[PDB]
Length: 228
Ligand SMILES: Cc1ncc(COP(=O)(O)O)c(C=O)c1O
Image (cartoon, rainbow, N blue to C red; front, side):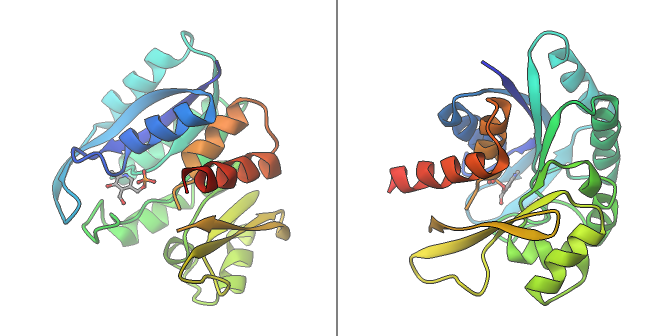
């Protein structure tokens, strides 16, 4: 059972964060390991605050997993601080053989703060070229690039060094479905939907199990359509 190591925050209410990573990775067929980036204080309605994990304790968790478990993929969600973004980049550069799924979490779904967005956007520059796949929703895509046109923003992310981008949402969305577009090396590789879209951890698990990107993304949609 290949392992996905998740650099993710803890949401006590269990709606998001490393709990959702654990659930998705288990359903993908892989094993989840966790390097907790923050203990948040939040529920479905608001974020009250959070205590970011120090860079030292973050790397200590990650390094405890290294050597014990067969890490094949890293996934990141909430990182909280620019220190933790830098620590993850340091970790990834020490392990270029790991695949990496970057979910560029800038805000909570409730709207509450999971860190200062402007400085997080600037710090994410370092992680963009390291990712096997970046999974921005349309808000995250625009924030990372400073570009409001989705097509132009996607291309800008590739100019910034992205290798593959799964854009969640776009001009093809409807009340029943969010449309996802998988781009590889700047070119549209697969155009799909998703009934509703938190795909990064499930995709990471499928990548850990040896799937190609296209097959992993397809499995993730089948998983969500199976919930429906
Ligand atoms: C701690 C935390 N991580 C991540 C997310 C969103 O990413 P997922 O719910 O896919 O982990 C949220 C909420 O939006 C969150 O509060």
